[PDB]
Length: 480
Image 1 (cartoon, rainbow, N blue to C red):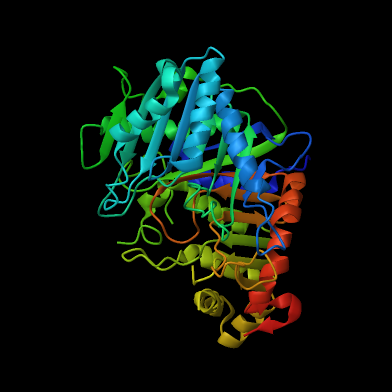
Image 2 (cartoon, rainbow, N blue to C red):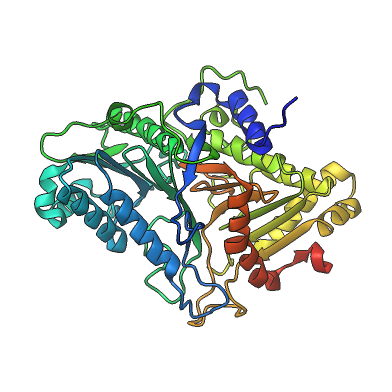
């Protein structure tokens, strides 16, 4: 018998086919043959960690931010057919807008005509910073003559006011062949023009998994175009006499996709609330959508995917997030199944590291108290729960230097949506682990070589400096 080289993806895949079988292909997809899109000078620069400083409370070395902007511009500049962008509102501005404009000009200068979609999600209150006809016109002016070659769709969307759902995915797909995704929403939101920048992470790849991201964006745009005449749901603006391109990706890029590398990946997203009510094909049989809505799970496979990635760990788990708990009533405070999965792992002796952003930006007591309470359910007593927790947990707030704050007095903040297990398989995307009912998207990658680069370039330094805030750290007998 033959031994799988992708045990973690195999397990996550099995769970996704149980939960969201009918969404396979569109909202989640397993592909082989991807390449993590790092040059030959720097093999790790698929890992787009911003700002890139470590050990330095003045963040001298901004190579991470500089590399992100250059990669956005380069990827768009190589477009020959399509450019597909999603983010949280507002529409691109500042340095991101400059990179979009420069890339689109470079593609046009090479003789290309492009279709371009730009989709943002809006909180129902934020409808000032979301005028799509204004953004279309400003981008068209900045493009100049290059605008003649661009068929543009720009939209802001809210899928549920009652259940607080709108797009939060952050994706750049070019020609359905290259993709960037992660937690970086904009230059200003991560305070990157600043001497207290926010730590964040994106990944860049090429290959079939970029097609997966395009199919996810086709799912959101099919709904957006179906609702383009409902002003409460969608504000839509297009160039010239262009239509609403519901399926730009299916139409302009194909399904069979050639391999560019040897990395297996599960692309996985969610549809939030108000796009699709249920996966009619699902036989899964496990208001609070995170913890008490089966139908919601079936159209939000990313939630089950992230819990399955935790469950697949045999040795150790590292979680880096803005938080594990939500502070947004009516949302629940935490994902019960996620915390139960983490508790069961510690009950087995699997190590769990959780680094979250400084509450200033305890936050920590909330996490350890909950893990302990879920462990008490499993182990039978608070004393046995403490034994399992103190012996297997590392819990801290984030720091990128030996200073407790940035040199300029602001606290460190972090916005990662990162999970890694067994120095093997990791998620980078836009989906927070705290309860949230938005459209989100990310990639789960199984590659020990890449996961070890993630250790060396991100998680090892993160812990070198964050351990100083730890309230629990089994490696030094700390358990306060």
